Image (cartoon, rainbow over all chains, first blue to last red; front, side, top):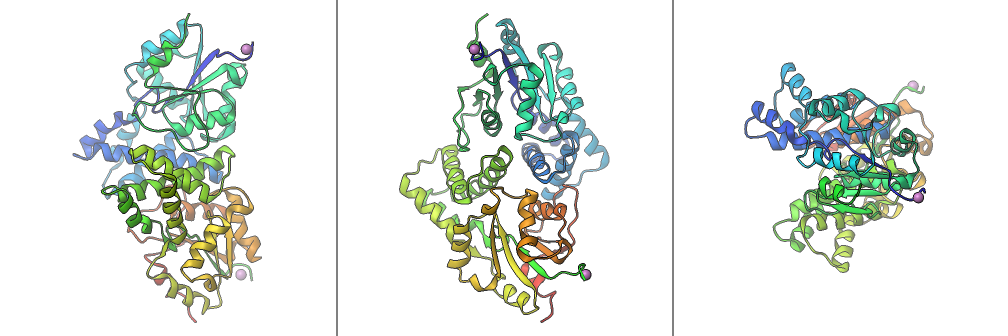
Length: 225
Length: 225
Ligand code: NI
Ligand code: NI
């Protein structure tokens, strides 16, 4: 009556879609160095979300992406012209979905559950990545931190899931591959499922995730129509 | 009147003291993985400070340091017992000052500049780092984030320098090697010095620092007795 999961809420980047899709195109421009440019870019992208929220300087995710691209190349000593910048950025809008995700999502819906994305992306960025993958019909709501002008893991961002879904905290399973994000949402109050894709270890940020699985299809296997 | 620099506020970790001085202890305990352990430990320490602040779950710098150390080891498959934690964690209370630092501090006071540390450190960790290196006399104020229960670069942290100095925003030159920290102060309102020791590039977080030098020694040489 208040205690059981009714909605599954996903982060977008790194749980549903692979942010290192962009390595292929970094590789073209910087031969030999696709992994490392793209590993740094993502890291500093996440850092800039954190720093701007802590500083009171919100700028949307596309902007933070560019700023992080620019730092990363200057930092690594690499020239990138305007056309490079433009193309590598446009590439964040067409990340590949992880291979378990489409079927996982059909089964979550088949088990009678609402589905939503809660993400640092702009409204546009989210619609591009989901739209470009053809999984537009798989989600009931697509929620952007645009709505509050603060990034994860600010507590006002997690609040948007329950307010959009009109559900209690215990009714929402928040799902993420990133520990620090599951941890934010758990402190907000949602039960949390950590996807441990990599065989790693949870953050020591004071909280143990309710559910741990190796992939979204496992998560899906947990529910019954 | 209220437009000229009167004090120099330093941050501690990575500007005054080398956070990688723990490297030799780490390499002894984890042979062949000591640099990695020292890099990741430090990076996850920073991320936990930013995470706790953003999630409203403050815990002091020493607690963060232990958390990060346990994460780091779990993540690398390195086992560590209770005594090894306590050992390595104690090493962080004894960081090594950069070469240039003590004499640069003697030279900045010799100009009638007030001098403070404003640090993410706890009241104990600050005293212990500054104290064990015998530099306690060179600072007029040791200020910890403990008085606000908020880590950098939250704007309330940067406020404490001007309140404790009883000075104007334009009369404090905040000095850090960490551009994200220099960036946070600048949005605060203080003029910043970015010390660029490693020879890199400043964050694309929308501000440009006011002075750049390569050393605190070089900075000290800009101030007349
Ligand atoms: Ni119930
Ligand atoms: Ni003046």
